[PDB]
Every structure is written in C-alpha cells, then in structure tokens.
Amino acid sequence: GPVIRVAGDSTAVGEGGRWMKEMVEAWGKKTGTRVEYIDSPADTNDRLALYQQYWAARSPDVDVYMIDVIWPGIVAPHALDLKPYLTEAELKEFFPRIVQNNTIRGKLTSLPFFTDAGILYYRKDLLEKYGYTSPPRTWNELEQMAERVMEGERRAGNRDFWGFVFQGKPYEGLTCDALEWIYSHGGGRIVEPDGTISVNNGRAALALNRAHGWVGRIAPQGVTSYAEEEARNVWQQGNSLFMRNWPYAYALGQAEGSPIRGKFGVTVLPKASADAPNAATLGGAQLMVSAYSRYPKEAVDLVKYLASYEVQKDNAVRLSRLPTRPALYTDRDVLARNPWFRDLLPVFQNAVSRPSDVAGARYNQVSEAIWTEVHSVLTGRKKGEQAVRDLEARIRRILRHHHH
Ligand SMILES: OC[C@H]1O[C@H](OC[C@H]2O[C@@](O)(CO)[C@@H](O)[C@@H]2O)[C@H](O)[C@@H](O)[C@@H]1O
C-alpha cells in the first residue's frame, strides 16, 4: 500500500525532528500505513531551498511538508488546497490569524501546527545574586544588568560567561531578531502591511546601532554566526544571563541534566521605552500536503492527525512549543508544565509579523536584504543610519512592480 513520506523539522534543532518522526510513525501504526521521514537542514531558509528542488521537479517523493509561517505566499502553487477537507467548525478550532496567514487567494495552503514568538530567557538565580528582582523591561536595563552580572561572574572565574546571546548569523533568524529590535524601538515593521517601506528612520537605525553595541561586549563576538542552537547551547551550559530565543528552548533547559534546570524564567523581550510596542516576532510551522503527492487523501488524514488536539498537546507538554488551538492554552496539563503560556499568551497573540504577507513570493529575497544589511551593522562595517538607507533602496528594487 502507499508510503506517506514527510519532510519536516530538523533533527539538527532540539528535539523537533525526533519527536516529529515519532508522531508520524505513530499515525502510521495507528492507521496501518507505511511512512518515511525525510530530515532537513537546521536553518529555515536552507530548508526552503531544499524543498524548492522537490517542488521544481513536481516530485512525488514527499507527500507532506512542514512549512514556515513566512512561506504560504511562496509555496502556494505546490500546496493542495486543504479547504475542501475541513469543516468551518474544524477550522475555527485554530487561531483565525494563522488560518488567514496560511490562506493565499482563498486557498488554504496548510494547517496551523505550532506557532512561535520571540521571548526573553533570564537566569533568575543570577538576577537575585546581583540584587535585581525583575527581568529587564527596557533594553538599557538589559545592558546594565548584563554588564554588572558579567563583570561579577567573570571575576569569580567563569571565563565563558556572557550577558546576552541571540541569533546574529546572516540567515532568516536574524531577520526575526532584527524585526524585534526595530519594532521595540518604535521604528516600524521594516515593510508595513500596506506596502510602505518604512525602515529608513532614526529609530530603526538606533535599534541596529544598539545591537552593534552588544557584539563582543555583553554578547560574544561569535554571536554574528549564531543561529537558534548556538545561542541555546551557550545559555544552556549556564554561560549567559539572558537569551533571546523561541519557546522550544524552555523544555530543553528544564530537562534532567540541564545545567540550568530550575534557574530560569521567560518574559517579553525588552523595549526602548515604556511607550514603544512590545516586540515578539511571529514564527511557527504549518502542515502542507504536496500538490505532487500521489496520495492526497491519506496525506490529509496524516496532517489532520499531526494538527490534532492531542498531538499539539504532546508538542506543548514535552517540547514547550506553542499550540495553534486556543483551547490548549486552558488545558490543565499544558499549563501545569508551562505556566508561562498563560502569562505570555497575549504576547503570542500580539506577535509582530515579518513582511511575508506584503512581499508574498518575493519574501525570501526581501529577508535576505534585511539580514545582510543588519549583519553589516552587527559586524561594525556600517552604521545603522547607512544600513537602513541601503536597505530601503534594496527593498524598493526587490518589490518594484510587486502588488499585494
Ligand atoms: O530562524 C528563524 C525561524 O525560527 C523558528 O523556526 C526555526 C526552528 O525553531 C524551532 O525550534 C521552533 O521554535 C524549530 O521547530 C524550527 O524548525 C520560527 O518558528 C520560524 O518561523 C523562523 O523563521
């Protein structure tokens, strides 16, 4: 009978790949269907390039793909329209915002699987050791606390200790960190949902200059090569006061034999001043049935299972990844394991989106311009003022003649 083949998530990032293959195998066993799991590179933009090879070839060799929240506009031609397979009631069990994200020109490209948002991880033991009673609310506070804790920890002999780690590698994760910096300084959304390229402004420039000011100071020099797992590993070995990362790092940092188990909390990222908006970049994964799958019916059943209440629950409890079902945020087991889901739910719902809706199929080119110009500031090659001006010019070229 059929073999349903699934490309999604990466065994190179936390436990996602392993857990996903487990879920797929469990569906296989439950239904008596053969399945195979195809692994992927770590970085989402590398995964896109890989999957684009299959799509270009109209390959039937993958039936289901896990896609990023930024992809529906790019991948729509390669997606089976899911809309005929779900009732309005079934669809309403997911966050409307994400269903809408995943719907391009009325086609439901994919089902919401897990969402995501950038948050601040902090060492509560260290904050208390140094006389602080709350995590920082402003970037200036983050910097002050990071300087003082680092000076103390370094003096006590931890030469590996830093104040802050984040994603500064030139790749999609940097676009995410940078949208947070820019938006939390009142500098806008880089490209606004109406199409306006707003990024050339003094607040955005300041946000980038501030980030530059972290590099090799409160953050490792090597941060300009860090993706999610590089940041996480410095943090999880106990060597960073703060980290910007996604929810998944929480369950990993609490696991038995984690050096930082019980020593950390999470909160909303800081901002420039009390009247700036809170910034958490919207991330996450959706499940797409390939337009080139020879087994659409079976693929859709697998996607419905993966997106189901109990599989999302398992994802939440075991991997601390965010459900796309509002009902799971009131589930007693989910909340008992992850009490911060309740506190940060409004942060997750107000998460700020990268400009994938407005750039559509050109999003990946837009994002590359963003991470390359941002990276130039992080390395001290350009000032934020120059970079945001060059970025405006590049995005104008990229999006000239594109309409949403
Ligand atoms: O790097 C940008 C990318 O970050 C997040 O996805 C990357 C991986 O992070 C996870 O651990 C989930 O938090 C893995 O499951 C992902 O493969 C975010 O979800 C993306 O939207 C974002 O583009």
Image (cartoon, helix red, strand yellow):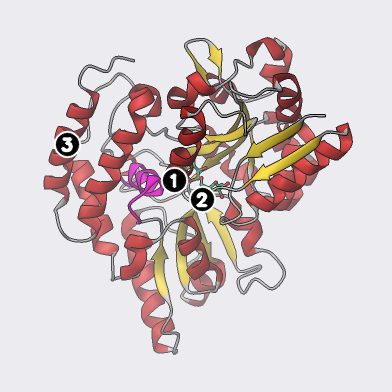
Quarter of the image for the N terminus: give it: top right
Between residue 127 and residue 380, name the one nearer to us: 380
Measuring 48% from the left and 56% from the top, which residue is drawn there?
A: 228
Local crowd size for mark 3, using a 10 Å CA cut-off: few (<14), some (14–19), many (≥20): many
Where residue 188 appears, as percent x and y from the top left, is 28, 34
Whole-angstrom CA distance, mark 3 to mark 2, is 33 Å
Q: Is residue 181 magenta?
A: yes
Q: Amino acid at mark 1?
A: Asp
Measuring 66% from the left and 67% from the top, which residue is drawn there?
A: 262
List the residue tagged with mark 1: 46
Q: Is residue 14 magenta?
A: no
Q: Are marks 1 and 2 in contact (CB under 8 Å)?
A: yes
Q: In the image, which is nearer the foreground, mark 3 or mark 2?
A: 2
- Against 260, residue 189 (above or below) is above
List the residue tagged with mark 3: 200
Quarter of the image for the C terminus: give it: top left
Where residue 111 appears, as percent x and y from the top left, is 63, 26
